[PDB]
Image (cartoon, rainbow over all chains, first blue to last red; front, side, top):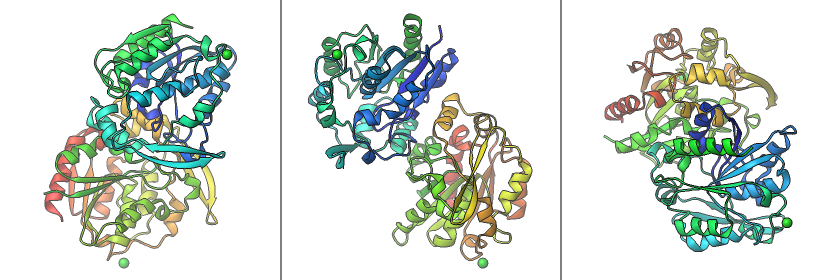
Length: 256
Length: 256
Ligand SMILES: [Cl-]
Ligand SMILES: [Cl-]
């Protein structure tokens, strides 16, 4: 079967991270949309204009709003992208055939929206040469960050080629997790986000979303299906692109 | 010898085009700077804010201004990047060891600055699915363009992999040649731009800067050295990356 995949990058990244996977999915006959989120990739906004993870998700919400009735998509989120999935599913949960989490946060409906991010920061407290700043938006102080190049090299793109790592150095931008805003956000709903089918894809060789964290997430909120990819690194859509495509084909064949 | 290479993308592109060449040059021991020009790549400006090729070149001029006395660079420009070189050399010609033109326009000092662009449009008049718009800045109507995806595929990235072409679809942005502004611009000077060493690199398999054009440019304004790369396509920094690095090493060893 063919699906319409909507690929959703993590914070400080852009659609460009999916530059290998997108053509491969298309070569399998799928429609693929790879979005830049607010203040990401070639989006014209700067992060200091963005006050929440919800506002950050605008391009995804807008895209879903523009789907004609009856058209469903499979959302694929990497790393912090699982939060954008949760947000989208609580607005457009009739449009979502399934969501695939790709070394991603997996929010739940029983704890506050910041819950898995708070846990991530316990398990991986040291972001190496990553720099931080503060800005104010909508009366709240928000912590912005710029991922450090050594963190990028060693922990996110560990096994990626120099030309891929170079793209990350060139294209990664200031971003934010909006952790304090998430902490005060209404919980994700059981009827929207809770109802969607959730496929959890991971590698135990991920050097930032470490096994303790990913296995903790799986036990905390049981996915409908789990796929464990052998080897690779955190950016499986670069290091294990063919394997990710294979998994996504199976998802397309399973959930509609 | 080692040099400091400053790599300069064409219109509608960004530093990202150099993502393969930059690490290779670095693996030879060079310092490499790959800039986003105004309203290009991750630069925060939109093109409608930019009134001239000179204003477009600001990030390059600013970068050159920030070089401490005595430090010289080798400028490397692709496609329309030769115009940014001319502009820079007329402000900072003591800072420039040489300029390498990479399937690039080669402005001169005898004809108006638009001369080689006017000629390019004669030789390659049909930009396929490229779209055009007009905006007004500083009292002048400027023609903006968005390179068409079929033009990209067939003429710029002809022999590049699908994953490279995908980057171009994701990252290329609205731009302008500022052709009418160039036409009224003061000529490039003999003392600045005219004095710099100029190395002309090309392939006769380029499907946009066709042989008639490139050979016309070489005869119009004799380069100090010409290198012809066999095969590849217009984006030689993607299809012939190792060959471009080899040439640039030789340039570094020749001109300081
Ligand atoms: Cl609920
Ligand atoms: Cl002169």
